Image (tube, rainbow, N blue to C red):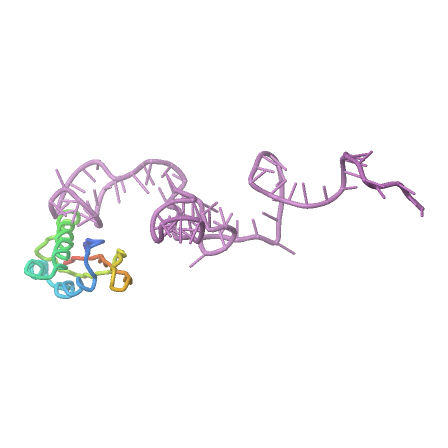
Length: 109
RNA sequence: UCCAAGGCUAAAUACUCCUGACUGACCGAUAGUGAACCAGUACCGUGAGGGAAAGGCGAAAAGAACCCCUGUGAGGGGAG
């Protein structure tokens, strides 16, 4: 069976998190945790948090053997964007989008 | 045909800030008032003035006790 965890609302771009998600998609739980704990990217702490929560759900709610799990699916979607104003020169203003991301991870044997 | 250089005179006529009742081949949230919502507000302007956006869980809050991951965070998964 497939055990899910969701991390709706990470304060980071989905583009910046998809690079991290592409390197753990399909890996075993142990290898994925190694990649995430030694990544230099900020998206990896979010992905590691969501993955650890999914593994905890699989151990606790579903009673699965953690040693045989793997990151069966993972995808990052775009969340709600905060809109801000950045002043520029000559009295002009640009809109700034502070993007967020939703991280969905599904572990499975 | 009528008697200025004295004064008056209701009704039938005009209108709606409003009160009551009732109606609509009027609108239904970019519409209908600018304004269904804490709106002439926020915001802009020295000022006169200009002037927004923004409604809906469910029949009933019964609005998720408790457990788990997490930083007693967010967010989620079970349970209900």
